[PDB]
Length: 123
Length: 41
Length: 41
Image 1 (cartoon, chains in turn orange, cyan, brown):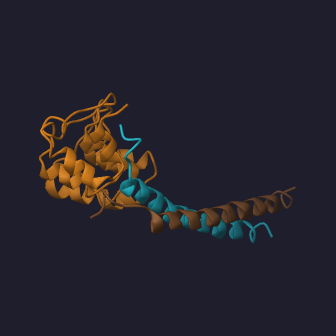
Image 2 (cartoon, helix red, strand yellow):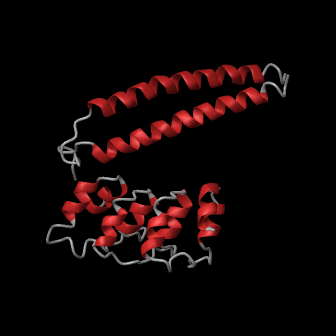
Image 3 (spheres, one colour):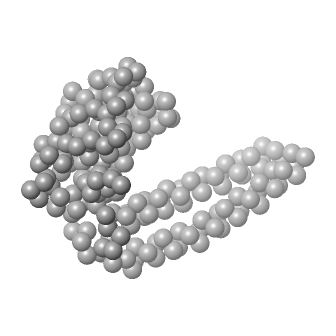
């Protein structure tokens, strides 16, 4: 199966995330990818959990990229979660204008999956 | 009659879509606050 | 044939809407009586 932090980060589950990052293991588990390449910062924002992705940024998570080369802005833009890209832009304003392995930005990924309410916020 | 029944099914699919988004918020809330002891990994 | 298939889809959207309202009553009951200990604010 998957890690206890990768389980807690994608299903909301706030007090379990705060407790796993409180342990002695909770220093190198925060930046660990899975077989798809996603850190807990990727899966928390792909699923649109906006107060779990904030605690991962107060503890200083690194902005790595998965096997497709996407940052947490582009994964949340594919899913149309508007409140979690207004928070990631307020603390990292340089993830908006980035590309991936296929060269697509966040406006490219929000139109491939028909997310009209994000396009008005991405622009 | 075709234009007065296609217009009726458009209002019905809007009610199904709004009921299903209010329910998807609650199902997603349950897994955030569900108690997991025996089946914990 | 158009009037005998638009009439058939009207009875199908009525069954989806009634199944979804009976289920929305149960999902809304779960959060009223769910046990919340670990994930309590």
